[PDB]
Each structure stands twice: as structure tokens, then as C-alpha cells.
Length: 19
DNA sequence: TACGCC
Ligand SMILES: [Zn+2]
Image (tube, rainbow, N blue to C red; front, side, top):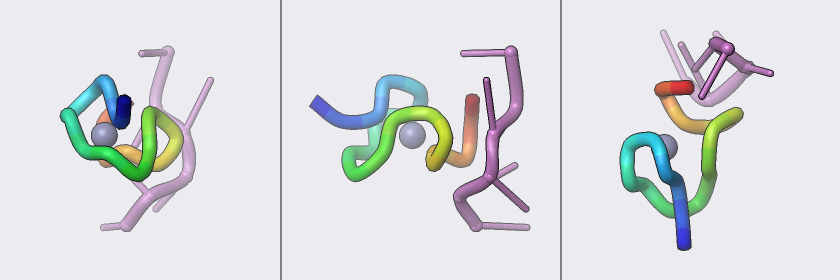
């Protein structure tokens, strides 16, 4: 539930600052 | 930034 890369919900990869 | 960054 959220971003897997950094750990910030609201995005996942595209939209992260990392991968 | 975020824009795939793989
Ligand atoms: Zn993220």
C-alpha cells in the first residue's frame, strides 16, 4: 500500500524521486 | 524536482 522504492504513499515508481 | 530513475 503506497510507494515500494522510498516508502511514500501517493505514488509508486514514475512519480517517486527514485526508480 | 520527479521528469520511470531500473
Ligand atoms: Zn517513492
